Amino acid sequence: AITTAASRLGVAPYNESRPVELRPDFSLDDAKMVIRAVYRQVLGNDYIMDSERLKGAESLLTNGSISVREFVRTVAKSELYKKKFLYNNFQTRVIELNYKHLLGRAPFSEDEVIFHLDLYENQGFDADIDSYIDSVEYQENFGENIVPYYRFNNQVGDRTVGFTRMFRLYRGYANSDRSQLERSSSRLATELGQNTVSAIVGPSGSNAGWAYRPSRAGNTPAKALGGTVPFGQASKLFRVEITAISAPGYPKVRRSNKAVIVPFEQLNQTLQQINRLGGKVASITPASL
Amino acid sequence: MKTPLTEAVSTADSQGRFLSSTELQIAFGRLRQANAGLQAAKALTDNAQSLVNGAAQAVYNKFPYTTQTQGNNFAADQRGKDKCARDIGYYLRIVTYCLVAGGTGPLDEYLIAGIDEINRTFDLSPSWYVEALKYIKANHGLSGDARDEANSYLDYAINALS
Amino acid sequence: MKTPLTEAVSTADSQGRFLSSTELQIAFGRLRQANAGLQAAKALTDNAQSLVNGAAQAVYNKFPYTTQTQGNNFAADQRGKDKCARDIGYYLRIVTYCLVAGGTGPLDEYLIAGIDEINRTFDLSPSWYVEALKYIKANHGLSGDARDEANSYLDYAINALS
Amino acid sequence: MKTPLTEAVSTADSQGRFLSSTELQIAFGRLRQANAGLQAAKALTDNAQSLVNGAAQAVYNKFPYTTQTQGNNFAADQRGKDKCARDIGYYLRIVTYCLVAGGTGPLDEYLIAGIDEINRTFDLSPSWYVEALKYIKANHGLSGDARDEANSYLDYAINALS
Amino acid sequence: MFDVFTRVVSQADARGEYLSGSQLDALSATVAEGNKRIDSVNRITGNASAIVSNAARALFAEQPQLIQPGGNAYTSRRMAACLRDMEIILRYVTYATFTGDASVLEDRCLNGLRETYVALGVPGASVAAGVQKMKEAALDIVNDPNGITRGDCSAIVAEIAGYFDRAAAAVA
Amino acid sequence: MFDVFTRVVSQADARGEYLSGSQLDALSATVAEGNKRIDSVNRITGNASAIVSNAARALFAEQPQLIQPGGNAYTSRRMAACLRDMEIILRYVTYATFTGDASVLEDRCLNGLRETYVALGVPGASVAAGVQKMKEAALDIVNDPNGITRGDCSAIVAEIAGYFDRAAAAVA
Amino acid sequence: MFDVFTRVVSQADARGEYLSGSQLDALSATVAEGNKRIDSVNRITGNASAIVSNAARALFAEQPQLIQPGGNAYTSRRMAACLRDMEIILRYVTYATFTGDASVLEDRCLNGLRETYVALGVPGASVAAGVQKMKEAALDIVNDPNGITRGDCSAIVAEIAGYFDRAAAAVA
Amino acid sequence: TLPLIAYAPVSQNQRVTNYEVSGDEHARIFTTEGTLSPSAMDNLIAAAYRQVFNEQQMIQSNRQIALESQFKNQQITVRDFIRGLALSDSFRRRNFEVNNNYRFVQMCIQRLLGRDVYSEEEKIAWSIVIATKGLPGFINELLNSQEYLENFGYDTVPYQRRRILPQRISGELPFARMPRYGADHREKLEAIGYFRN
Ligand SMILES: *[C@H](C)[C@H]1/C(=C/c2[nH]c(/C=C3N=C(/C=C4\NC(=O)C(CC)=C4C)C(C)=C\3CCC(=O)O)c(CCC(=O)O)c2C)NC(=O)[C@@H]1C
Ligand SMILES: *[C@H](C)[C@H]1/C(=C/c2[nH]c(/C=C3N=C(/C=C4\NC(=O)C(CC)=C4C)C(C)=C\3CCC(=O)O)c(CCC(=O)O)c2C)NC(=O)[C@@H]1C
Ligand SMILES: *[C@H](C)[C@H]1/C(=C/c2[nH]c(/C=C3N=C(/C=C4\NC(=O)C(CC)=C4C)C(C)=C\3CCC(=O)O)c(CCC(=O)O)c2C)NC(=O)[C@@H]1C
Ligand SMILES: CCC1=C(C)/C(=C/C2=NC(=C\c3[nH]c(/C=C4\NC(=O)[C@H](C)[C@H]4CC)c(C)c3CCC(=O)O)/C(CCC(=O)O)=C2C)NC1=O
Ligand SMILES: CCC1=C(C)/C(=C/C2=NC(=C\c3[nH]c(/C=C4\NC(=O)[C@H](C)[C@H]4CC)c(C)c3CCC(=O)O)/C(CCC(=O)O)=C2C)NC1=O
Ligand SMILES: CCC1=C(C)/C(=C/C2=NC(=C\c3[nH]c(/C=C4\NC(=O)[C@H](C)[C@H]4CC)c(C)c3CCC(=O)O)/C(CCC(=O)O)=C2C)NC1=O
Ligand SMILES: CCC1=C(C)/C(=C/C2=NC(=C\c3[nH]c(/C=C4\NC(=O)[C@H](C)[C@H]4CC)c(C)c3CCC(=O)O)/C(CCC(=O)O)=C2C)NC1=O
Ligand SMILES: CCC1=C(C)/C(=C/C2=NC(=C\c3[nH]c(/C=C4\NC(=O)[C@H](C)[C@H]4CC)c(C)c3CCC(=O)O)/C(CCC(=O)O)=C2C)NC1=O
Ligand SMILES: CCC1=C(C)/C(=C/C2=NC(=C\c3[nH]c(/C=C4\NC(=O)[C@H](C)[C@H]4CC)c(C)c3CCC(=O)O)/C(CCC(=O)O)=C2C)NC1=O
Ligand SMILES: CCC1=C(C)/C(=C/C2=NC(=C\c3[nH]c(/C=C4\NC(=O)[C@H](C)[C@H]4CC)c(C)c3CCC(=O)O)/C(CCC(=O)O)=C2C)NC1=O
């Protein structure tokens, strides 16, 4: 599991939280807790007012007229889910949102986006939502009676790209998917088309450099192609991701977030210049071998 | 790590409501048994070295083949005996952590969850650690409130290994 | 690329200033000779096939060793003649691009940067391409505003190859 | 000083290359604007004394406190009125210099550089000179290309002060 | 998360030793402090709606730019979200008071709250002023001598104030 | 960067083809519209300080929660940076209008600007609103018939509106 | 740097006076032969490589000790630097021709070049001879009657000759 | 090591605040902070070559091919590319081997910090930085110097700073004028047998 970095990455409130399962002869507070867990997960921790509470699907779940899987399906078919996530977003953003909500994980490969977008355009949003719900992964993870939940831990049949893209999608326990730095932009278009992985930046509070997002162009690549040769005498190279540089000003600082590859011997100086600048280090990744 | 305070907060957060009178009683039970848990943890801290050595010798007496045949998983040499003393010290220290915390949370997050892969991968019999925890059960010398709380963590570590 | 509009904007951006009347006059000269550049580019586009064939024949007339000696870099076979016609078509198409654009930027991004390593790696003499550009100078048929604008790019590629 | 010609050279110098057709089009726009700029500067030189006196009187009209409050920075006495008339004379003369040059370079290297700390350590409001330039923009009487290219300098100094 | 016991447990396990006598006596002093701690939790829980409503009234009284048409707290949805934010920050402050360690507050309440407030355009200084007002109300209500047995409670008041300060500092 | 000519040149080179007669006619129409383009650039440049000042005044009038203390345009340094940001975005809109293509605006201004604003906590929705105020000011000044020869200039106005919409969409 | 306009502007600002009618008429005359100025710049720019190569070839024909082993131009690197010096001097003569003033030539090319060639051991008389050979090559190329509109161009030819003589006198 | 011996600053134009509009005689910012075309990246690389190696050593043999390729891919910043130009073999042989430490300190201060040396004392102070830490140690000291940063930072090609004042035809002599070697290496090449007739 995730133990040491759980507090930093926000995994710990989901580490001590067990999956919510409705028993076959369930109590009323069990149905209410399934309702609350579904409204937190499927609607992505958005604030839900009483006007949009979806009383019909709640009432069908409360007497067992529908299951938890059918309740998740109903609240994903609803106009509230569509106006939260579908109508004002790119289709890749919608696909990764449905993956985070209904399956609790980030999309793995480009082929999943291909399948879901082709099925949406071929058969619409409801058909696509049904495909997330009627997936083998949904049954081996949640089935019929368990509310979907975020799956940060390693399971059978996952991919390690999904672990990094999960924190590209999950931005903290105090956070909703609509309330993130890319306001409507899909976070995995350049990560799934290029099949690349950006470094995991944790949420706010625990991580001072929480606000690093990469630009659409002019980004330093992750691996140092070249090694120590442009830097003279060096041993190891590290990509430092730096957030919120504002001490010199606009002529000097054009971009708040800067990613640079620096050696060991320049590491102290680089760290010192970040501190002097007032910048925040998001992550440091070993760029060379 | 689960604890009456942390599980109370996690539960009331799962319902998303303020701490009602239930969680106040939860922390009152925590207060009424936390002093006995701290006293038991202090007694185990003072008697820990003798307890670990005696538990290791109890395992070596109940399972003498661990001290005779060669192998990485056995205590026939000084390295294996040091590993066994370190393991029994880990078990006893996590029991003291559970006494301080007031629940099996240190056991769950540090020793219980995952010990099956430890026992299968490194060919370690859980009956050795069960006999060790039975030695701490029979020789910790606590009484009353401290005895029953400490025996709960020793049984739970025994119950997970069995 | 290097055109008056792009260079004026890049200069004003480097000095961190708005577009003064200097940059307005830069765009004024761009508008003044842009129509002549466009119609020169159209005349070269319509006469491009005859210009490339005549330039290839003029290079083979000045340099007959390309059409009689064996080698990858020579035009003795039909493949080498197709390569030379493709090269002269590349040169003429980038000349039309420069006539449309208003500066040597299409040459600097598509032809000038890296032609020395190609000419020394694939054993291509730049004097062949110089002679092809001299034929394009002598046979483009443009007059007045179009001729001086076209021959500026013809001579810019000539001085880059020489 | 900033001027199409000088700017074209500076670009070719920083890239270390000859003056391409981009630079020649920059010179062409300078040439087509220069006659209008010279006639505009001739008209402003002819109308200079009346425009300076009218602009100073318009500043005194909109800001009468400069003509009634005692102080070094104000025009209550004759020396302040002389300094003000010299200031609008400097403004109009450097505008004519920008007209002749064809860029904002005379304003940049003669007046815009360091006008802010001049206005704050001598306690001069820039809005006085803004209203003077509004009078020059309203009463210069030019038409066509001479009007717009003269106004581009007047609003350049207006945007520099404001 | 961690409470006051499991924080010391996790530190000792990361260091790999048994707890010394000073840590056990500090935890015994925490146990003696626990009745006043539970009184503080009960008082803030019992006056939570009054604390949230009065702090909202004071915040939108001295910062009226938030409720102005176009402000962040304008519209029933954004105001209801702001009131629920105040309620949840107060709830996690009571959670941190209950545990005796603030780990629930950074791990759940402030875990991405600044990202939320930056992304939505929520003025985090206004939220910090609101958390300041809830701190003032909660410390006035906990330290109220009426209807309770007398005794010094400056430690739990300073601890609640520290929880409120680190809640307000994470969004400001 | 690219201008209106080198965009078509780069597309033709990616095709590896000479420019067709439709492209030459479209670029000749661009040359015909070029005088109106230069007039639009000159008018926005000559009224740049008025556009930035009036747009900032109207922005912090309809959104007064940013100049109040604790706001993002509060303090002289922050407010000077906000006015400078408005001037910079307007300057790059004039650059994109001058080139006839939004390559310089997207690559030297809009690239990483949303990332910069969310890293600094700058509310990009408010910057987008200020960009719309500079939009309405600039399209009102450009479409002014006074002091210029009357003619149809709706394509240049729509192109400036497109650059302003690109600037507004790239900050939030 | 100055041009033919900004130079006269500089003496006018030194005297603090507006330009007279005669100065504006002289500047209008410079605008009138500006087309032949642009032709001269275009012809030297187009034949720059030929001018540099032919003048270097003739200079090392008349002065064989430069290409003899041990000479200042005796390597591939030193010959490349000497041809680069020719290209640079020709480039600055074209810059002075473009401006109509040798302020850029005296500023960025000529001032301090004599001490540079003394400190290197470059023979400045040989560089002056090569610059002179570039003068006859460039003046024969500029005065070519073929492929250009015919007219009197003795003023711009004399100006180029003056720039070349000033470049040769700065190194001799 | 040892702390640099103190040297007094001599008044130069870069020391005072620049009250100018950039305009004509401003050195153009060659920066990678804005996204560039490959042509603009090529002119930026040529500007770095012109600053470090001057115009003369812009030959194909002195082009750092892998350094250019890594710089295009943004593997390195502009400051690291300037370091790689200073650590280049051609730079070391042409400029460093033909000079003593004093004139090489003057050359590197002019071509990296963009300003002249204050006096002989600054050349003396950084020449022992050369003599102990090598050329890489010295270049690294100059490139980590706050001066280099507050002026050019990480993503700008260095340029001569404040060479010419506003409304002045002439200012300070350009840095391009300085030769690979001084008169001492000139007369040493004359003594070994070169340059005679
Ligand atoms: C057709 C003229 C050109 C072309 C197209 C092409 N597109 C793709 C792939 C994708 N296109 C999209 C676009 C959208 N996603 C959305 O949500 C929306 C709005 C709702 C749109 C418009 C996406 C997401 C993809 C990725 C999924 C996929 O691969 O199908 C491809 C295949 C990508 C590949 O190269 O493997 C192609 C070929 N290709 C052309 O040559 C024409 C210029
Ligand atoms: C104005 C309507 C809003 C506002 C602005 C504000 N901006 C900053 C700071 C910065 N802005 C930039 C932007 C750019 N970098 C680029 O390269 C370009 C285009 C070339 C742009 C436009 C940058 C880099 C900074 C930081 C560096 C600097 O200080 O200049 C601030 C200051 C924030 C701070 O000091 O931390 C402010 C206040 N603020 C508002 O409230 C308005 C919505
Ligand atoms: C030829 C076999 C194929 C091909 C090649 C091609 N490569 C590039 C660009 C780059 N190549 C590299 C690789 C390296 N740079 C280094 O320093 C090192 C080790 C020291 C390596 C391995 C890099 C970094 C680049 C980008 C930087 C640069 O341009 O120099 C291109 C250019 C792509 C473009 O459009 O920009 C090309 C064409 N292309 C083919 O088609 C062949 C299969
Ligand atoms: C499908 C391919 C795949 C891989 C490879 C993978 C790696 C992987 N290793 C993890 C954890 C881990 N990995 C280690 C490993 C080690 N610690 C050490 O000290 C040793 C150097 C080392 C053993 C060689 C540890 C200790 C953790 C848990 C970290 C934690 O507690 O937070 C996790 C966190 C998720 C989880 O544990 O459930 C992942 C995803 N996940 C995948 O899906
Ligand atoms: C882990 C516990 C937890 C926290 C802390 C939390 C915060 C939180 N506050 C939110 C919104 C919000 N919060 C506010 C709050 C305010 N606006 C103001 O002007 C005031 C200064 C302030 C109130 C004092 C507003 C207005 C929104 C809505 C923003 C919008 O939809 O546009 C949202 C967005 C989703 C939603 O609207 O439900 C979250 C997730 N959510 C949580 O589950
Ligand atoms: C645009 C959607 C929208 C609505 C509807 C809205 C209502 C609204 N009304 C409020 C207060 C209030 N509303 C009243 C209204 C009344 N008192 C009376 O005696 C009358 C009978 C009655 C009028 C019909 C009063 C007295 C308050 C102040 C409450 C307080 O400060 O405690 C408040 C509290 C915040 C504040 O003081 O502004 C909100 C949010 N806000 C919104 O953004
Ligand atoms: C389930 C609901 C419930 C609660 C919450 C509860 C709390 C509680 N608080 C107590 C004591 C106390 N409570 C306080 C608290 C304070 N004294 C002050 O003057 C301050 C105003 C204030 C801090 C907020 C003190 C000083 C004691 C006595 C010391 C102690 O017992 O720890 C006691 C000991 C019995 C007594 O003397 O009353 C209990 C049982 N009992 C219950 O049944
Ligand atoms: C260096 C300073 C300078 C500038 C900027 C300049 C621009 C300029 N704009 C022109 C035309 C024009 N300008 C416009 C523009 C417009 N018409 C409208 O009614 C709209 C309000 C507005 C769009 C903003 C039009 C329609 C023409 C005539 C069509 C054309 O020439 O393209 C002309 C042609 C000559 C004329 O008829 O005036 C010039 C020279 N000349 C100079 O010397
Ligand atoms: C932009 C104005 C400007 C110019 C033009 C200039 C000239 C100049 N010529 C140089 C070298 C040279 N210059 C020459 C030129 C010649 N050698 C001969 O024998 C011929 C007489 C002549 C060819 C016409 C040579 C051969 C060198 C190479 C010296 C060497 O590197 O050993 C150098 C030093 C090379 C270096 O530092 O790498 C400079 C600075 N400096 C400036 O600031
Ligand atoms: C962008 C490329 C470009 C250039 C460079 C260019 C130059 C150019 N030179 C011109 C004239 C001219 N050029 C010359 C030049 C000369 N006459 C001679 O017999 C001498 C050999 C020679 C001096 C080198 C003369 C005399 C005129 C006519 C007078 C004048 O227009 O100034 C003209 C006026 C139109 C014409 O009659 O041809 C143009 C446009 N036009 C373009 O599109």
Image (tube, coloured by chain):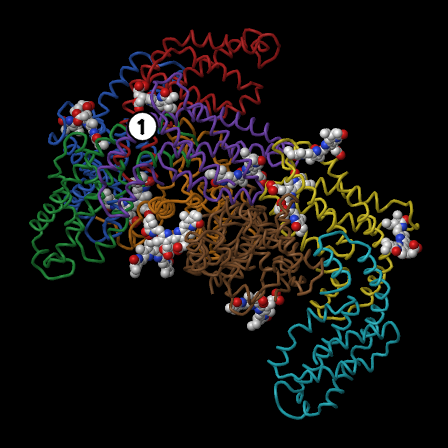
Chain colours: A brown, B cyan, C green, D red, E yellow, F purple, G blue, H orange
**Is there any visible trace of residue A30 in the rendered image?**
yes
Q: Report the front residue among H115 and D29.
A: D29
Report if the beta carbon of the residue with label 1 is closer than 8 angstroms to ligand 8.
yes
The image quadrant in which ligand 8 is located:
top left
Whether F43 is drawn above or below A61: the answer is: above
Give the mark count.
1
Q: Where's residue F130, x and y in %?
A: 52, 32
Label 1: few (<14), some or many (≥20) within 10 Å?
some
* Nearest to the observer: residue E19 or residue A121: A121
Q: Amino acid at mark 1?
A: Glu
| Image side of residue A195 versus residue A70, left or right | left
Specify the quadrant that holds the N terminus of chain C. Answer: top left
What kind of element bears circle 1? helix
Q: Position of residue F22 (x, y in %)?
A: 24, 37
Q: Identify the residue at horizontal 40%, vertical 21% (top origin).
A: D152
Identify the residue shown where x is 42% and y is 28%. H166
Chain on which label 1 sits: F
Q: Relative to A239, does residue H34 appear above or below in the rendering? A: above
Is residue G10 at least partly visible in the picture? no
Name the residue nearer the viewer: C8 or B116.
B116
Image check: H116 left or right of A79? left
- Is E157 on the left or on the right of B10, as rendered? right
**In front of the other: A94 or E141:** A94
Q: Position of residue C77 (x, y in %)?
A: 10, 59
Instruction: Locate residue B3: give its quadrant.
Output: bottom right
Residue receiving disc 1: F33
Q: Pinpoint residue G19: horizontal percent, then vertical percent.
A: 34, 14
Vertical relation: E19 (above or below) H58: below
Q: Residue furthest right?
A: E150
